[PDB]
Amino acid sequence: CIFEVKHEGKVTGYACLVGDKVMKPAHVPGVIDNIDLARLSYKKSSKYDLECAQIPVAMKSDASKYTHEKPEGHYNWHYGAVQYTGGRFTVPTGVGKPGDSGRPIFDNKGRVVAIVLGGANEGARTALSVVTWNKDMVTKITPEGTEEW
Amino acid sequence: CIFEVKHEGKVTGYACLVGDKVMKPAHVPGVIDNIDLARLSYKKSSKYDLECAQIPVAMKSDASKYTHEKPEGHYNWHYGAVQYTGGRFTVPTGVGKPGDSGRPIFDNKGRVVAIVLGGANEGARTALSVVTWNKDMVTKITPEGTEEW
């Protein structure tokens, strides 16, 4: 469910299969490294820093489910645990870096709860800028001091 | 009917109101410099290098007409005349340059016949890569050696 985005031969970030969409953070430079995904029509929102295409039918079963449900505790991503408390996702400073935008954060059922956009270095911890969902709609939540990834 | 696209305070290219659509070359970085247009959701695809939205009600009457009709001769753009011969729009080399993507080309009735994407330097003249109309449908025509502008 995760695809590299590349520019000039380098991985710049990721797109992920979420719900029935191919989702990519808009700010990530380059092209998704699948020629068919790269050619789809994407609905682009500057407000949410998001581009989303309808998932190819052949890939529909590979998509992750997703949810607005975000009880406090810990969640999962490529690098390990993501804390969620007081409406903030945090990780240890240094785990994430430029090149990690587009990676999903998941609950233990495998449901996507957020897509990483960047991180604000707050000392020992880094607070993530994310696309995430409330019960009604998508949102973008960006801590002060965020560096886009 | 023509708007600047800007990124980091710099003009990066242009978007046009044509028919029912806001038309911007997809590859141009930045956001359209208009309060209404910036807040729309766009459909973006590499197929024609277009990023489009429905024109807001308030702006519909400002849209340009368009046509598929491209008899040979000369057409009009920001910098003067554009030659059209053998299926190719050409201008003198150096008249258009990086930053001129999204500018429209018009006939003498004021109908848009093409939107500039880039140019192929052919020596004294440059052949333009364009979106243009075949019957009712957009198409992308890109001379060999095109640089996206």
Image (cartoon, coloured by chain):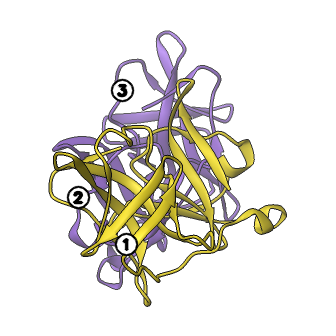
Chain colours: A yellow, B purple
- Asked if marks 1 and 2 touch (Cβ < 8 Å), the reply is no
Three-letter code, disc 2: Asp
User: In which quadrant of the rendered view does residue B16 lie?
Assistant: bottom left
Q: Position of residue B131 (x, y in %)?
A: 56, 48
Task: Look at mark 1 in the image and give the residue it sits on.
Answer: B40
Image quarter hosting the C terminus of chain B: top left
The reply to whether residue A76 is visible in this rendering is yes
| Crowd band around label 2 with a 10 angstrom C-alpha radius: few (<14), some (14–19), many (20+) | some
Left or right? Give the position of B41 relative to B30: right
The mark lying in front, picked from 1 and 3, is 1
Q: Position of residue A41 (x, y in %)?
A: 62, 60
The reply to whether residue B107 is visible in this rendering is no
Check residue A41 in the rendering and tell me which mark sits there, or answer none. Answer: none
The outermost residue toward the right is A58
Q: Nearer the viewer, residue A50 or B106?
A: A50
Q: Position of residue A106 (x, y in %)?
A: 53, 66
Task: Look at mark 2 in the image and give the residue it sits on.
Answer: B33
C-alpha distance separating marks 1 and 2: 12 Å
Task: Look at mark 3 in the image and give the residue it sits on.
Answer: B97
The mark lying in front, picked from 3 and 2, is 2
Q: Please tell me whether mark 2 sits on a helix, a strand or a loop.
A: loop
Image quarter hosting the N terminus of chain B: bottom left
Task: Using the image, name the chain to which the residue with label 2 belongs.
Answer: B
Three-letter code, disc 3: Lys
| Crowd band around label 1 with a 10 angstrom C-alpha radius: few (<14), some (14–19), many (20+) | some
Tag 2 or tag 1, which sits nearer the N-term?
Answer: 2
Please determine whether, in this image, residue A125 is positioned above or below residue A73: above
Task: Give the residue displayed 19% in from the left and 43% down from the top.
Answer: B8
The mark lying in front, picked from 1 and 2, is 1
Marks 1, 2 in one chain: yes
